[PDB]
Image (cartoon, rainbow over all chains, first blue to last red; front, side, top):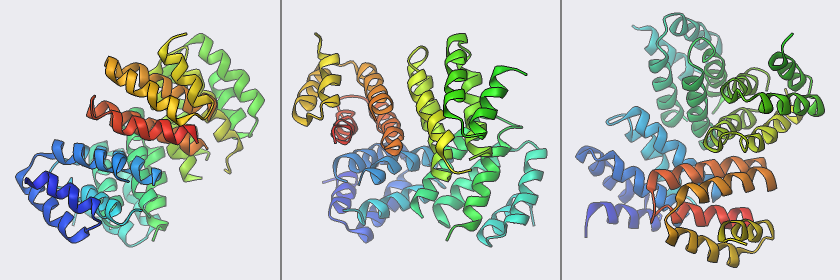
Length: 85
Length: 85
Length: 86
Length: 83
């Protein structure tokens, strides 16, 4: 058990509410790199090729914005990846 | 009251004419970074996930071109985001 | 008259053959940055938002490949932009 | 004959299994840049314009992640391009 793996599991399980609970904690802890890395693996490994591609746009946006505003593209992507096939 | 904020409200309000009025002014002033930052936030927050992703491409184009030609992709995504859901 | 403006005009006029005629010459001359800048301006100015956004992907691919191989993404996009609605 | 061109040929021939077999070997060898180069060329030369663009995103993810985990977007693109 750690937060970043449970984040991933909740996204694999299509659980928006849990994924965003964990996202908020990851954001507040402030390591943007590992969120970004994780979301790209999930987008490519677990998920819809337009959705996979879009995870990269959202990560570039998160990286250009930086924390705290990075939470906006990331929240979007999390829900995107949760509702996806 | 602030130009960059009024720019943001214009786009949320779906007002192309006013959004473009403010863009031309942010452009004249040379603050490429704040335009780009605001567009990505609006794209991911207020908005059509393809439209969200496409703000990143536009911003990349803007950054690679630099001002003054950056106004071109920027005006394009301003209109796109205005007319979007 | 220069070739890069004539290249731009051909794409505006949806003329695949002329645009590829010019691209090949621009590719041979080898100023990749100038070709990339112009395609992004054409993509966002003259063109279909998905097609405008794809010019960025192709330019990124062209920069990663470098010349001579950059001509592959570049040709694909000149065609994409030629056919695309305006 | 070499692995990389054989890799390309099997993607050009729509052979998912062989392409994945070559990828795993290219991954084992540790040279990401070469995989990335070939993928972009196939996607642009042999191929949807959306499938072409989308290979650049996969490549960006691959470079951002590095190997070993870069194998994840790369496998996705190989399959994507095979079909």
